[PDB]
Amino acid sequence: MKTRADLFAFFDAHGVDHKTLDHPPVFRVEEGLEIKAAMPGGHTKNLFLKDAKGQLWLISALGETTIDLKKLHHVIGSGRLSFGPQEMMLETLGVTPGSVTAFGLINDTEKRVRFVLDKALADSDPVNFHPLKNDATTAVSQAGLRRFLAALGVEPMIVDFAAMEVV
Ligand SMILES: [Cl-]
């Protein structure tokens, strides 16, 4: 299971530049606003899902993007979707509760996790995610995110969640 230092070593090897802000885990709306004020670009949510057929899925989206989980399976070609179990979140993404992040894909050595990217987040620059724990927020450019995914061999499925279409 990878550390933050391991993640940044991976970024460095592959030319993904980063800027990190350390902070207590956010439980207050004022603190969240302060972070967003210091860190431009897309601020994310990252949903760890398991479908009725056993396939794991990670959706990274802007926080405000509405995701209709009742109907999404028709769009992405999955079985009906539920939230995945915490144990698999640890095993495949190496993160603990409340710390889900696209950067956790560095831990998915069996390539069990299919990755869905909100079109609105693909069209954000920069983008911000936790560096494997929610006591920090890490910015990378949009190109950097794509460089990261490419280095892992992860092809994102880009979904327009408003139109409910793969794009
Ligand atoms: Cl870049």
Image (cartoon, helix red, strand yellow):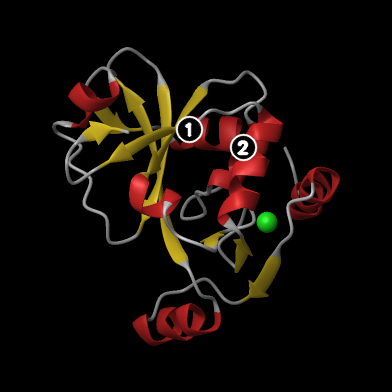
The residue indicated by pointer 2 is 149
Residue 156 — which label? 1
Relative side of 121 to 38, left or right: left
Give the residue at x 41% y 54%: 123
Give the residue at x 61% y 50%: 143
Looking at the rendered structure, the kind of residue marked 1 is Pro
Measured as percent of width and height from the top left, residue 28 is found at 38, 81
- CB atoms at circles 1 and 2 under 8 Å apart? yes
Name the residue at the top extreme: 53
Q: Nearer the viewer, residue 27 or 6?
A: 6
Q: CA distance from mark 1 to mark 2?
A: 8 Å
| Element type at mark 2 | helix
Q: Quadrant of residue 164?
A: top left
Relative side of 86 to 133, left or right: left
Residue 94 shows in the view:
no
Q: Earlier in the sequence, mark 1 or mark 2?
A: 2
Measured as percent of width and height from the top left, residue 19 is found at 69, 69
